[PDB]
Structure formats: structure tokens, C-alpha cells
Length: 330
Ligand SMILES: Cc1cc(CNCCS(C)(=O)=O)ccc1Br
Image (spheres, rainbow, N blue to C red):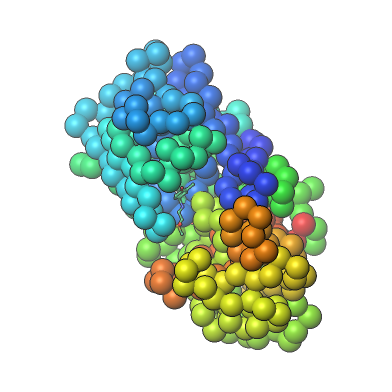
């Protein structure tokens, strides 16, 4: 089997991407944030505290003939940005882009943090990191990908995120029309439950490439590119007037600037992030200070190749017995 679904930016800045997902019978379509940095499929629901719902579509298990309470199971997750949600668990039929899993754990939110209530465009998350991070207790649950894997034509999914445009998530096959050149594969460590890999270095604009190992994770559910402070300082030093602002919470730059590109290494290959991808626009409406898309990881404990980086590539998440990542230009 295979599946293929379009993923669409939630706003003009590409802060996140939403993908329609069918849950239940008859289908209830929710727009979920596919997150390769977490392992819970959770949704706004008929159980979510009413004051915490503001425009999201909800899953109502009582309307699904295939929904079963997963008796006694609860979940609770906290994300690197301070956000959280928690609740109870149903099993139900979940389909993505024509690929169906029966008995998927669908984590129904009772509580969500402010950051979720205030995003009417995101009806929940679909985690695609390793199932070892799943937060369901007392019986940990599998991701949609792990449940689908055995049925797929190839144990892979691919992320093809657009810059200010829709893109695609495919499951079970590699669309050889979707990229240019060849795919470079690189080793993955699953020790922290992430798609963790080691970049071979970086360049800023037309500068020389610096060969240096940068461990990090491929994370579709993080907007920006978070890298070591040394790397990030070297980038923003090439932008007149850029500075780190503790008041704003990262590097800002004059909105009048033209940003340089940023290249990262994948083995002997190179992925180039155009400068425009690193512009996240005014810090507040009408400001002439703009927020940067490359930020320091210093206050995180991990480097994160988020959407700024991933949208510059066709990315293969190879879930074979020995997992690997692949990157191609596009
Ligand atoms: C939309 C959304 C997604 C996620 C999942 N990714 C979080 C990545 S980080 C580096 O910020 O911890 C959290 C919160 C919101 Br709000």
C-alpha cells in the first residue's frame, strides 16, 4: 500500500503545515500537523475543555462506529516551546492520503495549552518520530507510520514541504519526479527517539564550506532551523544590523536586508536554503525589525533541522530495520 497527501502552510510565513487526516467511520477529517519530532497522534475532540477550543475542528468518538475507548490509557505531552496537551485514548481507523490503519491510537485532548487554542488552523498533531517517545500510559502506543509500515510497499515516508506553497507527504514510496539529482542517505541514531543525524558542515552565502559535525534532528513540527551559537553568529554576522535580542527572543534583522543563503552538508552533498526562506517577517505588525529563521539551539540541548531547512529538500525518512535519512535537492 501507499498514501499521498498534500500539506499546506497555516499562514503566509510557513509557521507550520497542516495535512488532512480521516479519522473514524464515517470519516471525520481533521487537519493535523505532521511532526517528525514527536510520537503522539492527538486531536482536539468533543472532550476538550470548551474554553480551550477556538475554531478547531474536533473529533467526536461517539459519532464513529469504529471508535473504541482504550480503557485506562491516558497521555500527557509537553513540547520544547512550553506547550502541552493531555487526555485519554481511543482506537479508531485513520487514513492519510488513501493509506488506512485500523486500530490506531487517537489521543483525545481534554486539555491543551494556550498556544494550541490560539491556533484555529491546527486540529492536532500526528507524530512521526519513533514510537519509543509515545506518551500513552500504561501501554505505550505506536505511531501511524509504525502501524502502517508492514503494509507499505517500502518502509518509508517522505516530506516535501513547500516554501510559501503546498507540498506533499508520501508513505510507502519515493516519488522520483519530486527531486533533482540523487538522494544522499545518512545514518540515523534512534537513541533519543528522534530522526537524529549528523550534518557534515555549513556555508554562509557564497562563503567557503566549513567541514564540521553537527548532530541534530529532522523535525517537521519545528518552524525554524536551530543550530549551535557559533554557526548562527557566523550567519547573522553577514547581515548588516542583525543582532540577537533577548527582549524578542532571538536574532532579528532589518526588514530592508537581503539575506544570504545557508548551506548544510549531507555527507558529500549540500542542501542550499535560499535567503528568502530565512525571513520570518516583522516581529510585530508594522515593525521594521524582522525575525530570523536561523536561531541558536544553545537553550534547547539539541540542534533542530526544522521546516526552514527541510523545505529546501526532498527528505526521505527510511524506517527500515536500520533507519536512515535521505536528502535531495528539488
Ligand atoms: C504547532 C505546534 C507544534 C509543536 C510540536 N513541535 C514543537 C517543536 S519545539 C522545538 O518548539 O519544541 C508544538 C507546539 C505547537 Br503550537
